[PDB]
Image (cartoon, rainbow, N blue to C red; front, side, top):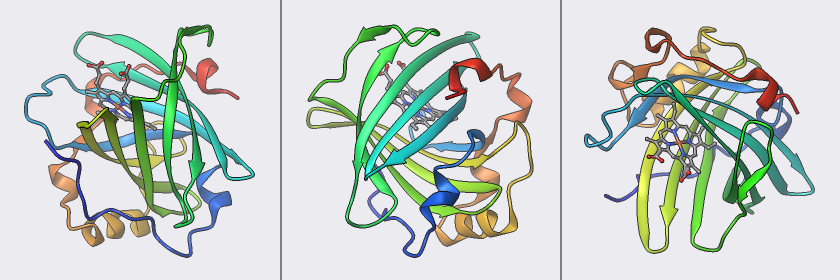
Length: 180
Ligand code: HEM
């Protein structure tokens, strides 16, 4: 499995629109058929002087379990795109594993407006691409994605109907974790 290659950030994006509020994933497209569990995700990205920090949450909708991470990376010279190393943490942000040199993710912002975003995430370990996920985001749980972001899906060469919608998954969020 190789992460999707036709990936670079949309030029002209206002970073203040992306690094704002919090995001909830309303739709995701995970390329790997062997990932049968479905997830919900929410995260709160912030940037200062080209360094991105973000508290990240996953909910496994089948097992009904949640896991927590803090990513830290540098903005690329290309725009709204960054490769993050990450801590693994508990719900209180106590560190279980510090960031390391072999585990990372690369997030690329493909569209972002006042209400909504389309981002791509490649999770890697060493020489290996572990996960490839496109996510449509909104600022509130089950809010409708913007027309501009729906266009961006099509612009990315994708079909929104092929994504998994998170509304029907029985998502549970931890809004205290993502606040900050
Ligand atoms: C609903 C959208 C998403 C789904 C379906 C999804 C799916 C997954 C799955 C299946 C795993 C592997 C879990 C395991 O077996 O340990 C995972 C891990 C991971 N995801 Fe996501 N993900 C989502 C959103 C995101 C977001 C938005 C980010 C970053 C902003 C992200 C970053 C990561 C990272 C860093 C890992 C590795 C965590 C670890 O190894 O402990 N994912 N994701």
